[PDB]
Length: 100
Image 1 (cartoon, one colour):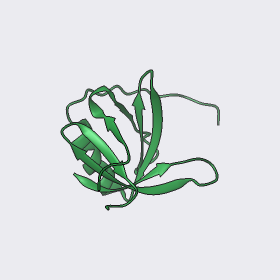
Image 2 (spheres, one colour; image 1 turned 90 degrees about the vertical axis):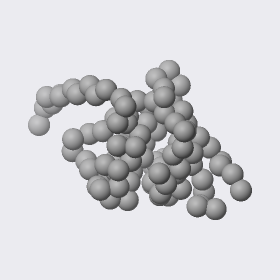
Image 3 (cartoon, helix red, strand yellow; image 1 turned 120 degrees about the horizontal axis):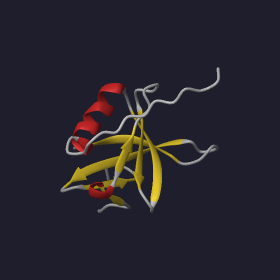
């Protein structure tokens, strides 16, 4: 699978588009669909977090190593990425009650 996902940089530069490519359990990310990758992550050790409130955002977390925040172009895209990235994983759902 391949396509654009936005990567959260920081509060100032915010969402920046990158080209992502999933192959053999490795999610690689490039500046543009155009020589070799400029980065990658091992899906095998990665957890994926998604909030019920939002339909495009997702968070990749490598326990003990790091956490990032991604955003698909649209809701349909995100689902597509989720199936590809996480169909083999188990899910754990938590609900939190907070002051209004």
